[PDB]
Image (cartoon, rainbow over all chains, first blue to last red; front, side):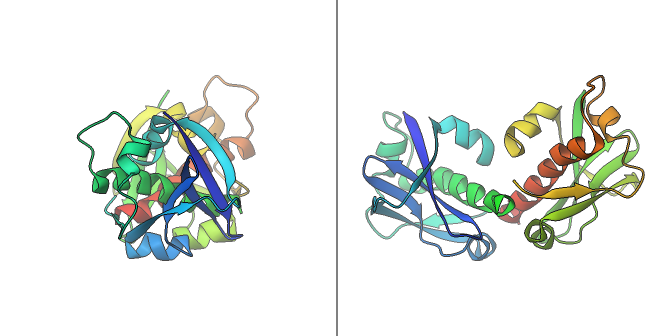
Length: 118
Length: 118
């Protein structure tokens, strides 16, 4: 399963997402510094609005090997239950909360490092 | 040349260095956010004071593949001229300024991501 990383440029940083079909998984955040420092994040899964930019496509491993191999916690109210099926298909023994942890760290890390690219 | 990454924990982030023998290359910075956002950094090479913590040892590639593969600029007044010989031995066609760019991004990136580990 090649995974597509996407982003929206918010000028002072890039806000990243994972695009699966016509859906984007991303953090419900307006600023990377606030999210990083407060240490908690809420996930959204949202219809693709057409305003996302491709970053790269790669096996999940390309990302988790960077950003995953931290104390931040990641939650979702509704509609993110599909994340294990979407990003970790076939693999049982992976819960919502865990999958969210892995993908959350990828997105947080990429957004934090984007401070250098402004 | 296996490369040793070291750090000092400043509580709200980790400040990283490369230890070569009894020397530490690191950024002359008191805070990661100030350095990241201002977009410039000064290198120091300092005698090891005995107060650094081992992070990991690995070929430079383990690091550059993460943090290098950005617009930040990296300078040094004196005494860092040894960085190409120390961190990139044998390899000609690598200047002070370049070597500093590669190592600087490793240190900046690791310190930025350490915000997640507090």
